[PDB]
Amino acid sequence: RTFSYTLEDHTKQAFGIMNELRLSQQLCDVTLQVKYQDAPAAQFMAHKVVLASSSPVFKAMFTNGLREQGMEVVSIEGIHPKVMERLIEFAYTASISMGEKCVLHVMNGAVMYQIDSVVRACADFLVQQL
């Protein structure tokens, strides 16, 4: 006779640890350098495999069948640092939070990164405001 087991909380617990490693800057292999209009420059370190798991655009950007030695710097354009921050957090935690009046900027960043679940959620909000 065979024998299976599934831990239902596993992926949640594991993303908990991945987020701690991001915040401690351990095992990170990408730095996103975000410059937007005249807002001050910001950097966010991350794990390519986690970004790729949440965004088809990151996935295509990092999958070039001939990956670098370690730490890639990526220049990002036309998205505000706070918006990037919240999308990175979403990728690592499955949750996003914003004031009523950032929701459009967030949707703008989410479309650009093809993070479809948050595009949908923000679209729902905006329509309810009518």
Image (tube, grey):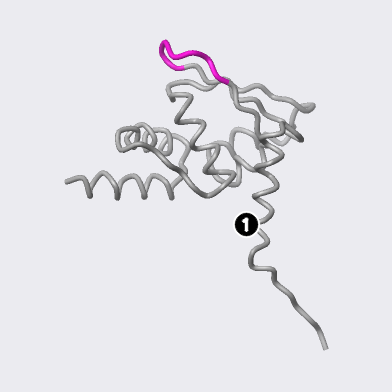
Which image quadrant for residue 109? top left
For disc 1, the marked residue is 12
Give the x, y percent position of residue 111. 40, 38
- Residue sitting nearer the eye, 108 or 129: 129
Residue 3 placement (x, y as % from top left)? 79, 81
Which quarter of the picture shows residue 11? bottom right
- Above/below status of 68 relative to 4: above
Please identify the residue farthest to the top as the structure is shown.
Answer: 38
Q: Please name whichever residue, 21 or 34, is drawn nearer the observer in this view of the structure.
A: 21
Residue at figure coordinates x 35%, y 33% from the top left: 102
Q: Nearer the viewer, residue 63 or 85?
A: 85
Where 102 falls versus 93 (above or below)? above
Q: Which residues are magenta?
A: 36-42
Q: Count the numbered circles shown.
A: 1
x, y (%) of residue 24? 71, 33
Magenta: main secondary structure? strand
* Residue at left offset 37%, top offset 38%: 107
Q: Residue at x 35, y 36 (%)?
A: 99
Whether residue 41 appears in magenta in the rendering, the answer is: yes
| Residue 34 locus on image (x, y percent) | 53, 20
- Quarter residue 65 falls in: top right
Amino acid type at image mark 1: Lys
**Secondary element type, mark 1:** helix
Q: Is residue 6 above or below residue 18?
A: below
Dot 1 alpha-carbon crowd within 10 angstroms: few under 14, some 14 to 19, many 20 or more: few
Locate the N terminus by quadrant: bottom right
Q: Residue at x 50, y 16 (%)?
A: 35
Residue 45 is a magenta residue: no
